Image (tube, coloured by chain):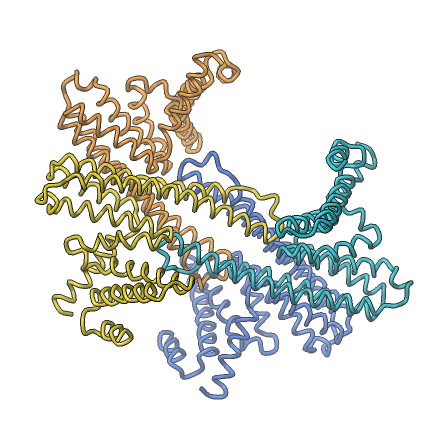
Chain colours: A blue, B orange, C cyan, D yellow
Amino acid sequence: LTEDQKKKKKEIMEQESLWKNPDFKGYNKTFQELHQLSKTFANNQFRLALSNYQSGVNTIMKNRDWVEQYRKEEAEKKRLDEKWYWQKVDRKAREERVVYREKMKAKQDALNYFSKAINHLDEIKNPDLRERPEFKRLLSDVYRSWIMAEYDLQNLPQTIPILELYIEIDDNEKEYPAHKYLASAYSFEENMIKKTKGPDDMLFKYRYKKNVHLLRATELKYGKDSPEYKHIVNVIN
Amino acid sequence: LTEDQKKKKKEIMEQESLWKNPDFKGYNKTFQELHQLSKTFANNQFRLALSNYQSGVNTIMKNRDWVEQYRKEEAEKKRLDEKWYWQKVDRKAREERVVYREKMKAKQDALNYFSKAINHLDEIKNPDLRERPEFKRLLSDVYRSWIMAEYDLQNLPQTIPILELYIEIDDNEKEYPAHKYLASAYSFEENMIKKTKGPDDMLFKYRYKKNVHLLRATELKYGKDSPEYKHIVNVIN
Amino acid sequence: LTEDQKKKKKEIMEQESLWKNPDFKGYNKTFQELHQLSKTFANNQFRLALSNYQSGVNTIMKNRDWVEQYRKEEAEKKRLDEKWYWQKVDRKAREERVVYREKMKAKQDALNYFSKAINHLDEIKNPDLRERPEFKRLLSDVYRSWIMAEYDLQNLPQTIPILELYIEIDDNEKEYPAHKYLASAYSFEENMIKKTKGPDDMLFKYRYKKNVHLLRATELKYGKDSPEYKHIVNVIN
Amino acid sequence: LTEDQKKKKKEIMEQESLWKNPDFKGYNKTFQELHQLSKTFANNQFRLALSNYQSGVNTIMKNRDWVEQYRKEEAEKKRLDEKWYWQKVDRKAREERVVYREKMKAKQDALNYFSKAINHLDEIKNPDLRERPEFKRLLSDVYRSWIMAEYDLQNLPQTIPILELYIEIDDNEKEYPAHKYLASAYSFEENMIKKTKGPDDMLFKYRYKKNVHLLRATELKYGKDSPEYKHIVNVIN
């Protein structure tokens, strides 16, 4: 239990908290912090980027309520034409499709707002302003919400370019969850190549990039030359 | 409200009760009645057929308990690796497959016992004994449980020969549910032909047989020259 | 279907929407509107009252998430010591008490913030500022959230002074839900007097005030000299 | 792991299986065994006692289906008048009371049949016939179902005379669950005395009898001079 290992355990928990599924307490904390950063930044394009990012998260939060209400309404129905096991299976499959289609619509609306937030941050041309902690914090939040919205619906290939942009920001590369999700997203791509009998150069590329992020995630949370890091190094070597 | 129409409404309800999903009260009533009929019949092959039929229904009843217990056990688990919507969908799909596989195993065991019940009734060669009400009652119960087990798992083509044997017994042809299930089973076959671009002679045969049973089911529960019977006749004509 | 009757049906729906249980879409709409009114008002005490009101609603919204998460955690447990019906009853009664105690704690925190919002509005002494639409809108929202928090936990007597202050604001007296909840709250008090064999002057007072608000709620949504209004007048007369 | 300790672990599991909540597989096994014992016994009073015992268990089994169907029907209703937390609490409390009242009715009908089973066994006067394994097996099954029906509804004092009659039969005194339930039932009585400030002679009697059965249950499943038996002896000493 070194000063650095205690700092590690606390930091991994703080990083896991950062990547937590959105809820009310987290929404309130995020937007209270972002609105103060907007006041300190006093930049019109940042204000417009924040407004779009907030609308995008609001789309997600509204959809979370829609799904609970829809499931409640479906549970409260009497099913007179459900004598057979296959009928109840079919009905649950139709309900799951309605939920999936509404979540896809909410994700599309949310990504349109995130894309607009990015368009406003692209308008901040001054390199000194782009290096500001306020700028990097909002950019990280937009990308993280974007990655999570795609990941939730199993759009793992779509998360890869966003996660790669995210890890380039400040010290985001030291984030164990960013590496864990990147590793899984590359794994999905490797598996898609193996399943579709795709080209070997792509298989090896995806396998390599999965291993890079799997090794980095292990190193970050367990440390270099620990039983977890040494083990992953041995299988790859 | 004629003497015959009052007799019709009461009879359709009694027929719907006959085709009800198996529960404890129905099981107890069925086997108490069958065991008394076995005593009156005093025939060793009937006794052995009844024992196999009972074992087959017992398989079904035991499986009903297994499914409720399995669903209860699955609901009582903490899911630490279920952050994403697609993960919960996948997990529910795995649970539904375990349920489907166990129901298929119970159906196979139940049909093996029903087949053995039929083998023992086939050993009763004396034509006077085969015409006995006890014989026809057990034969109807075996076929009805067999049809229902297949129908529950969406094995509608498999129900067709069994339903056709069932309706030949005594006055079973006057049963609205037997015609309703036959009509749906022929409809499934017609739809399979249309979906697989099968031969026209089969399409027309299945369409015709669906219409025969749809018309008969309507005639039986609503009566000839009623607004329901006249309507179905017009669409077919 | 007169111009006024069409205006009535639309208005009752808008009033029912105003008194709807809090959800994310409603929270977002309320605080986006209140924050713009704060900008137009440009008053420091209004800003502080709005901040306290928002913290109070946030307490309620956070508690809604806490309850769903608690119920989920309780459902996901295996109960090895629950062989008997009375054990499952007792366990559900303990879960309901934990929920009730947490909701009472959240209500107490929310009412402390609403009380602080009212303290800041009490600091706005200028009679011209107290007559502003921004002032009356925030005051109505604070009282309505306060009434609803108390009503949710069955604190109906506590809602009476708040509902009476609420109906005095602008045209809030024309609100069918305000009269409906007042009528029920007075009914609870009348029933408490009858149950505790309380004094007749209190029984008659509560009965009268229940009737006043029951009659007003009927008049507002069905109109004067309609089959609903005429009926209530006849029973009271 | 001695020959006796392996015999102990297997036997405690067989005893726990004997006291398991009734389900279809257990019902089928019990009545198939009892009907064969009836054939070997060839006694008319035993046949009538078995018929009453079966009707009593059937009452219980039918009620298990009734409760699941009632809960299903209640879950499938839309509740338009359930805006408030207290309304949903009240509604669930009304549902629990309907379930409790139906279970009490089924228990009363089941105990009337068990009492009739006992009346028929009381008619078997020949001491040689009363010592028969068939007689003792049916008597144990009647008492065990009777105890369990009472225990399920928290009628623990009512179970005490039945458990005391049960443990007198053959080697039923070697049954760990019989002692465990007796200990809990005496504990309930001790707690009722402490709660109602009842007489000390009753408190000490119930405390003593609770300890007798708690010590015996420990001795039976863990063995004499084991860490579990030695411990319970020390607290009592």
- The residue at the point 82 percent across, 70 percent down is C45
- Taking the image as drawn, is residue D50 in sight? yes
Res. C158 image quadrant: bottom right
- The residue at the point 15 percent across, 34 percent down is D44
- Front one among C131 and B129: C131
- Front one among B91 and C204: C204
Q: In this picture, is B14 found above or below A187?
A: above
- Taking the image as drawn, is residue B204 in sight? no
Q: Position of residue C124 (x, y in %)?
A: 85, 68
Q: Position of residue A62 (x, y in %)?
A: 63, 55
In which quadrant will I find the N terminus of chain A?
bottom left
Q: Position of residue C18 (x, y in %)?
A: 73, 51
Which residue is the extreme one toward the left? D128
Judged left or right of residue D146, residue A88 is: right
Res. C46 image quadrant: bottom right
In which quadrant will I find the C terminus of chain A?
bottom left
Total number of numbered discs in the rendering: 0
- Front one among B163 and A158: B163
Q: Position of residue C52 (x, y in %)?
A: 73, 68
- Front one among A137 and A72: A72
Judged left or right of residue A128, residue A218 is: left
Judged left or right of residue C66, residue A126 is: right
